[PDB]
Length: 47
Length: 49
Ligand SMILES: *[C@@H]1O[C@H](CO)[C@@H](O)[C@H](O)[C@H]1NC(C)=O
Image (cartoon, rainbow over all chains, first blue to last red):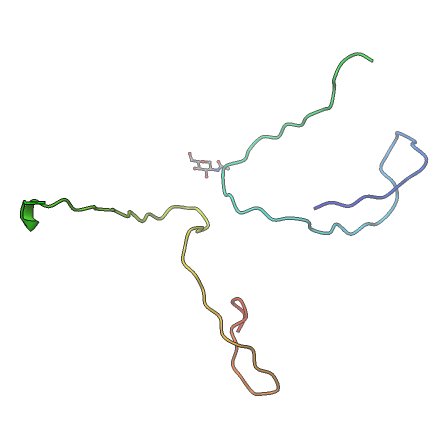
């Protein structure tokens, strides 16, 4: 599920005070075991 | 070619079905009929009846 909204002001303190409905985008039929989560970042070089 | 049917070569293909905890993926086709309107008809639309 995913959505996007703008905020203009950064204020890196807390999530915005607002309601939003999360619309589905895709469904996946493989039923493999999942127990842990890991994420990536885009870092190319010092620049 | 000169050998008999008993000694002739035969091509054999073996299929092996199995069931697991998977959500079922590889099964066969479902056929559909025409669509009728304005008549009292029992229907089966993709599992809803
Ligand atoms: C993970 O796989 C094992 C099989 O060793 C199974 O017993 C278990 O239900 C699966 N799921 C989780 C969340 O452990």
